[PDB]
Every structure is written in C-alpha cells, then in structure tokens.
Amino acid sequence: VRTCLPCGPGGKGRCFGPSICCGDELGCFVGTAEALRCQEENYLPSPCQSGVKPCGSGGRCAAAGICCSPDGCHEDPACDP
Amino acid sequence: VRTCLPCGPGGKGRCFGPSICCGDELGCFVGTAEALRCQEENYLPSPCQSGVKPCGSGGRCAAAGICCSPDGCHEDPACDP
Ligand SMILES: N[C@@H](Cc1ccccc1)C(=O)N[C@@H](Cc1ccc(O)cc1)C(=O)O
Ligand SMILES: N[C@@H](Cc1ccccc1)C(=O)N[C@@H](Cc1ccc(O)cc1)C(=O)O
C-alpha cells in the first residue's frame, strides 16, 4: 500500500490523515499549517498508508510514543523506540 | 484554575498535556518541538487547564474542530467554530 503524501519541515514527515502530519524526528502536527498539504491526499484515487506498526484502534505509530489514525493521535508506549 | 503554560509560535499556544500544544489559529502540535515546554507543567505544583469547552472523554476543545485531553487529540465536531 502506497505511503501517504510527505509533509512538514524538510518534507521529513508523512500524512496520517487529511490534517495530520507526523515524522519520527518531528512529532505530529494536527490541524496546523504543516498539515494543510495533507488535504490533497483525499483528492487522490488510490488508498495510502503511513507508518508501519499498527496501534490503538485503527491507528499507526507515527512518531516516538505516538499513535495516529486519520482522526487523531494519542500517547502509546507500544509506539516507543 | 490557571491556564497551562504558553507554548508554540509566539506564545500563541497553550498546553493541554506534556507534549500537546494548541491554539485556535495554530492547531495542535503533538510531540513536536513546539510542545516541549509543556512537559514542564509536570513540575508545577498547581493544577492547570487549557481550553474552555469540555469534549470527548476528559478532553477540551483545543482548536477548530479538535478535542484534546492530556494524552491525545482527535477530530471532534462539538469543537467546531
Ligand atoms: N487517497 C486518499 C483517498 C482514498 C481513500 C481510500 C481509497 C482510495 C482513495 C486516502 O488514501 N486517504 C486515506 C486517509 C488519509 C491519509 C492521509 C491524508 O493526508 C489524507 C487522508 C484513507 O482513507 O485511507
Ligand atoms: N501542574 C501539573 C501537575 C498538577 C496536576 C494536578 C494538580 C496539581 C499539579 C498539571 O496541572 N497538569 C495538568 C495536565 C497537564 C497540562 C498541560 C501540560 O503541559 C502537562 C500536563 C493537570 O493534571 O491538570
């Protein structure tokens, strides 16, 4: 499954939702300017997925100790380095 | 009680948790550098609370359509402008 659009500082992050941009060395931007770019993903035909490890309920580790779904992010030890 | 520590671009944000910094016109920074000072609240012996309207489970509207508790943020219509 294709990875979602890249985003944020130095394009070092990937989109996890229409308005969620994360990276292991960035943390997560939720609804900030850095994640505006992620709104483009929804006008793209194919499905995308960011992150590798499944966590929480339908989410994916997006950053150090952080688990995100396209709807939000929460703290999750399972996502620690 | 008092609002939590200021954070983010030009002190416009407030802390909703150890690694959560949000502002109405900024969105939320979760685990990003912008939220680093937020972990300092932990050292303050007085209780704090940001946001004005409660939402979700122990959360508070932190930004346009976004609800955050000290350990996460999710899209929440109740928190819409
Ligand atoms: N490419 C978009 C839309 C789409 C969804 C499902 C099937 C085909 C196309 C997409 O994959 N959206 C994601 C969620 C998402 C992730 C990042 C982002 O910046 C915006 C949306 C999905 O629904 O799987
Ligand atoms: N000052 C801290 C610790 C404390 C909690 C309760 C009573 C007395 C002291 C604090 O108020 N923590 C918050 C949660 C929080 C908010 C913002 C932040 O950056 C980090 C933690 C609380 O429990 O109300």
Image (cartoon, coloured by chain):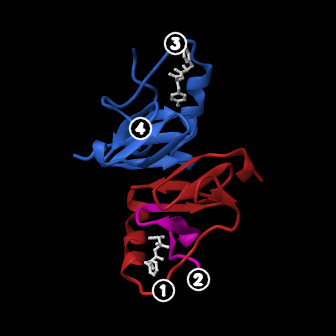
Chain colours: A red, B blue
- Front residue of this view, candidates B61 and A24: B61
Say which residue label 4 marks.
B56
Q: Identify the subunit bearing mark 2.
A: A
Say which residue label 3 marks.
B46
Q: Is mark 2 within 8 Å of ligand 1?
A: yes
B16 falls in the magenta region: no
Q: Identify the residue at image location x=55%, y=50%.
A: B32
Front disc: 3 or 1: 1
Gap in angstroms between the C-alphas marked 3 and 1? 50 Å
Name which of mark 2 and mark 1 comes first in the sequence. Answer: 2
Q: Identify the subunit bearing mark 1.
A: A
Residue type, mark 3 in image: Ser
Q: Do marks 4 and 2 both belong to one polypeptide chain?
A: no
Which disc number belongs to residue B60?
Answer: none
Say which residue label 2 marks.
A2
Q: Few, some or many C-alpha atoms within 10 Å of disc 3 (few <14, some 14-19, many ≥20)?
A: few
Check contact, mark 3 vs mark 4: CB within 8 A: no
Gap in angstroms between the C-alphas marked 1 and 4? 32 Å
Gap in angstroms between the C-alphas marked 3 and 2? 47 Å
Q: Identify the subunit bearing mark 4.
A: B
Name which of mark 3 and mark 4 comes first in the sequence. Answer: 3
Gap in angstroms between the C-alphas marked 3 and 4? 24 Å
Magenta segment, which residues?
Answer: A3-20
Q: Is mark 3 within 8 Å of ligand 2?
A: yes
